[PDB]
Length: 84
Length: 87
Image (tube, rainbow over all chains, first blue to last red; front, side):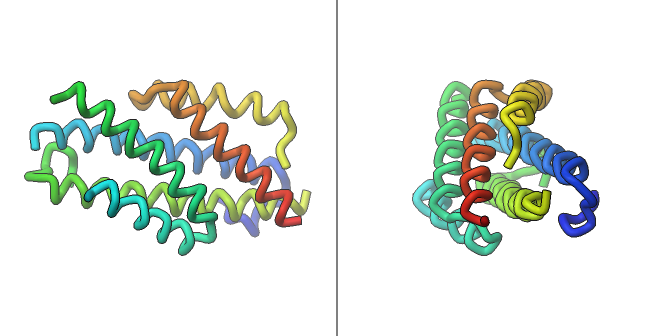
């Protein structure tokens, strides 16, 4: 995948973003496999600040990114409840 | 460890933190691409093509489409804003 600097035009950039967004979706997909697998077995309060930290380390607005994981974490918690 | 190789919440959570980090790093790379793009903000048409595709990706991966499309609607929307501030 051409690096941001090796992108000659908008075409290169958009295809890179599509690959990244798909990586994210596939990662979310894997995430759900792990969560459901955790069914047979403070956390949330520890997880969010941690993701906010990672966000800052990666040059992203921490609050926005933490808000995204707040949405993700609760969705997976709600999904897991039906797998009790 | 794969989902089936996790012996407890310890392995599960390590795998989940790993995946969440991968996502944050991906969002980071994503921003490097949007910023590099300035040299040339996505048009309403690009956005309209992008969202349905991400919904489709969600389904192929066993995820709820409305939910995932909403997440990406937020990501694109926020990045467009950041793209304007980066100018």
